[PDB]
Image (cartoon, rainbow over all chains, first blue to last red; front, top):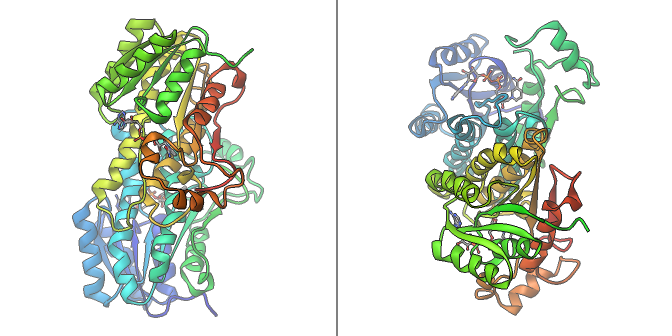
Length: 245
Length: 248
Ligand SMILES: NC(=O)c1ccc[n+]([C@@H]2O[C@H](COP(=O)([O-])OP(=O)(O)OC[C@H]3O[C@@H](n4cnc5c(N)ncnc54)[C@H](O)[C@@H]3O)[C@@H](O)[C@H]2O)c1
Ligand SMILES: NC(=O)c1ccc[n+]([C@@H]2O[C@H](COP(=O)([O-])OP(=O)(O)OC[C@H]3O[C@@H](n4cnc5c(N)ncnc54)[C@H](O)[C@@H]3O)[C@@H](O)[C@H]2O)c1
């Protein structure tokens, strides 16, 4: 069975709750010594603490992916704690609706959080993954990187670059032994903006009939970073119930 | 005929030579009042001059897409001269091969140069186009934006961003009577490119191109005139790809 991560070291950025927290637990159960990592270092310690409870291998760290210094620390910490880096899940990020006349700080920040971050980390992680003989990079994109809508300037155009970054950098680090893929999630039960009348709307145009649950992405991350996705690269697997939200 | 820009006002960044030249040069003969702009200040003026020379209305001005001072200056300086804004051609842009380990300074700059700026100017002209009833914004992408190859991270993902921005902000300025399009151009045999091109490379770039010739700056401009004129009045959000059916 190829859906495992035996003898693997995985950084997961942004993994204190939600998808990150989920990818972390799932990779740790898959057999990977997880470097849990978030901006809020205590929940990051808890997720890594939790994985330790269940018999897993993990250390929990602080890392504002937007902080170059933090990136180089996390990268250094992983090697100092597990000896190698073979998997990186760039899940930290975010976004939302903004007006067309939004302030640019909001704008440029999105490409710092959602793109600049994960590209730089991929740069820092790449040569180590090479030494191990190969690795895998997973960028958590969004359905906004595909979709087309009002008030979607920043959140849309940012995450569409992360897709198309994923497509191309595969050609760069492919030769070093590295796969690069992307998961574009739909809406996830992760809630302050949710109400049952918006729900039926969100559930319109969603063929599978439900919103998402973070183990949905987490399950897809395991696949795309495991040997079951061993010849897969340059891709963007959209997990959104057959629809938009 | 609807392939015209009669009594329109077009801010056209990056327009001192090559493409942006032929855009601003073509929009001229299409009865447009052009604001020829480029980061060389003489370069824009020299072009507005030949336009005025051949029959046109055009003022030469200096703008650095990646400079806010220059952006707010171009909106007003066009308005003060023609009253209104009806066309914004964000032809100013850049990029090319870059190794994977490139310095983050290079990576950010291509976004500053290709996205952020474009987006900002188009924030600016959008309520002034709204006064004139409506207009057309045009971005210049690149086949880097859909294509995938080695050393394309900065060049490729940024134009990609440009593209899907075009796809999304058209829902925003779409009710303001504005339409957003973009063109991904293939390789354009310009004067700049010719001087570092060669027949043996050109033959390489061209095999796997079905039409069998390089692009030329007018080919982008013909498409730019169509996309900005009423002859595409119900066309918006689009990313038209002028590359002869292939990649280069
Ligand atoms: N959850 C969704 O509905 C949804 C939908 C589409 C796309 N996404 C994508 O998933 C990713 C995150 O989804 P989410 O809802 O789990 O995220 P979120 O923003 O709700 O936060 C999840 C975790 O990310 C951490 N985090 C936030 N900023 C960080 C930073 N600068 N550095 C490190 N960690 C940080 C938080 O501490 C938190 O534990 C984003 O990249 C987003 O584009 C999510
Ligand atoms: N082969 C091609 O020419 C080709 C192919 C695909 C896409 N494009 C796109 O066309 C656009 C540029 O065309 P080009 O290749 O002739 O570029 P270029 O560099 O050859 O010249 C374009 C003009 O833009 C001006 N310029 C440069 N930086 C500027 C700035 N910060 N502000 C304002 N003006 C500036 C330059 O002076 C130049 O005259 C870019 O968006 C590029 O991505 C070009």
